[PDB]
Structures are given as C-alpha cells and as structure tokens.
Image (cartoon, rainbow over all chains, first blue to last red; front, side, top):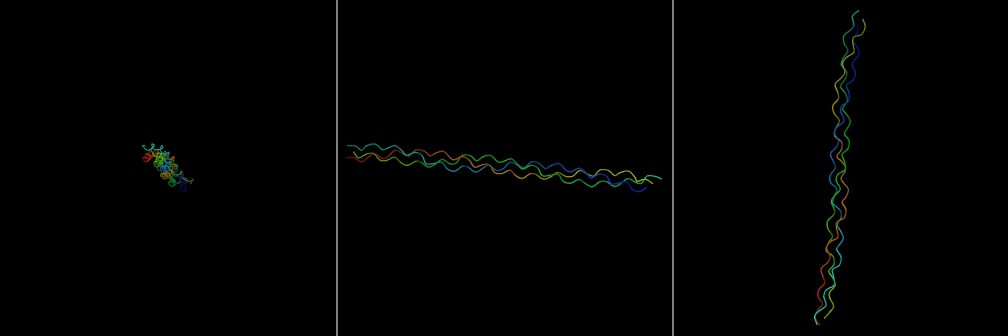
Length: 45
Length: 46
Length: 46
C-alpha cells in the first residue's frame, strides 16, 4: 500500500519567562522652604 | 496486500508565546528636603 | 494495499521570549519642608 499519513504537528513551546521588574521611579519633587525664623532680640539700651 | 510504509513525522511545533510583562518598578523615594526658611525679622532698636 | 501507519508526532516547539521589562515606578512623594530660618538679628543699640 501507499505510505501512511503524516504524524501530528509538535506541541507549541512553553511561554517565555515573565519580564523583569521595572526601574525604580524617580524621586519626588523638593519639599517647600521651612518656616520663617523667630524675631531677633531687642537692641541694648 | 501488505500495508504501506509508515508515514512521515509531523512538523516541529511553533515557538511559545511571550512571557508576561514585568511588574511595575518600586515607587521613587521622597524628594529632597526644601530649602531653609526665611530668616527672622530683626529685633527692635534699643 | 492499505496505507501504512501514521507518522510520529513532531518535535515540541522552543519557548517564547521574555516579557517586556515592567514600567518605571511611580514618582516619589514630595520631600519634607526645609528647616526653619535662623533667628533674626538683634536690634541695633540705642
């Protein structure tokens, strides 16, 4: 007789590995200036 | 009549799918401290 | 004669590629306020 039918195609490959975690975010914007300092002492008499 | 010969081997499988996208990175750390505040006003004249 | 037996199964495919790198993290919180200003100058003498 004639040759038999071709075998089934192979299974697909495994999924690839999960990606690496992203880079750290950039640091925040600067904080505000501090409060105003206290009033100076009165002058000497 | 005799059976024929064995059929040919199947084709190689397809490559697998891409992996999942990675996790988001860590949040950045807090920003720099702000500048020193304005100097106090001077004291009154003596 | 009748056809021969079926062929064997093909080779398994190769793995898929890695996923994309994750997105960058979120921007950090704002920095702390700076220190208070210095005490004002003493008033001039009378």
